[PDB]
Length: 628
Ligand code: NA
Image (tube, rainbow, N blue to C red; front, side, top):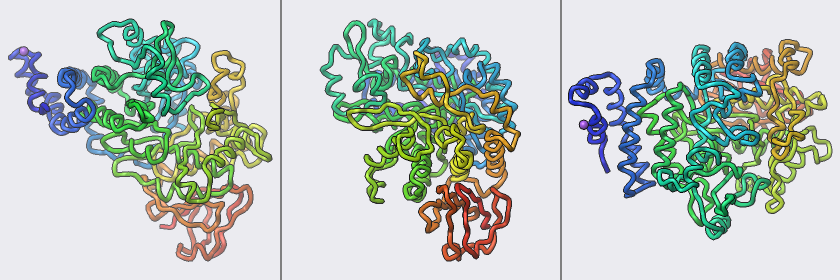
């Protein structure tokens, strides 16, 4: 394997003797050279573990390093300052000062210029992180909400131009908000130039995707593949007009990129550098679990997938240190955490906590949630969870069957209950969600619907507002970076037209992708409305989280409340949080509280609470007690 010093001498060979002398003395080269020596070993080791003695490895690597140097040289000075700032502050992601939000540019603000006008509101709310949904060119009509990319460089004309995107990012940074965008690297749309050229037989794009002559291999692979969108097609393949079959894990118009080809890694690394230089702070690594395939396996979470992500990480440490990764791995808990690491994805979605928050609202019992917070919350140094209540996607019940069995709970039976409950097919349920991808062959199913729709706000359930407060309180205080699905802060309900829209009717996820509700946002300062109650309560919790150091970091220790309806945990051995998941008053006995201070201030309600006597919580009440 080649070493950093040797490879750098070749990077400089493009310069004449005179130019070379100047480059070698430049500050940019000095920084690039230093980072190469420190991080190149990791890049080489990761690529070697995947490609081994592949003849294309060396040539691909040298091409990638040459591009990395040009990219860093071009990188704006202001971004280079952020690179240095984060190099020496790896835990910026763990600060309690961080609070994020996510929204679709078109649905929330019309276009990029409109989004820019919403920045003052984001500052009003207290956001320091903003994830904008897929912004680039995609197929007209059906594109999986922009996740079928037809071009990684051209902005969706309905949203604006690449110039408008630069202005937006600059404006976000000026307002103290980090820009977060998707890195859709597992697949492209079937209309992407690479796909068209690969399928046409262009040698330059040979083996950029997985294309087969017939069903022989597809049938073999399908013996172990999980269906993500069973409604769209069976297994993981789709047939082309000419009769061939292509690997399509998701929709048929999304073709999986072939990472067994080193040139594909180089191509996508180039796209990552492009996004990095636009000023993006965090890249959401979409579908990380699926980037490596192997016959006889589920083609999910394979070793090479992790290695490739660690290789991408090293490229950023060398050419754009400020860029961090957010892993999107909605899989088994044992597998979710394997993507999180300082050298892989520094942060990642926490689907287990999210799914269990909803589980607990339905069952009124905190058993599973307590178990998860006790054994699966703490992470390695310099990494953090992204805690959320809802997202642009459906809710999947990804808790571990093994964990549940230990509590005497049957995974399959329990998911049946949760699905029926949340789609209003269970006596007395307050939820008004909609089914997503019910699979007749497996019995699995997911749930669509906004947070407000799922807690009963559509029918004005008197407990709805308090349920929303409880859910968000936990994502905001357990430790990690909380992500608010914009619109939830004013109680936005399901979209009213998706079910009859021919481009959306077969994808219920659109039920929870409503447009900015002018009426509700105009009521956010009125305490007599649901919108005003939800907004002021969430804003208050955000204010407390960001100003109180007791919430800093991502570690927690659970507290046994001795009441199956009340969750309890402690942050920094100084903040005791209690959350009542019952619609009835619930008590934490004085006996249980004997070791606590006699009195403690509650940050939620603002009153002083006595802990040397029975503590009774009202339905869905949350308490944030300062015990130190
Ligand atoms: Na030369």
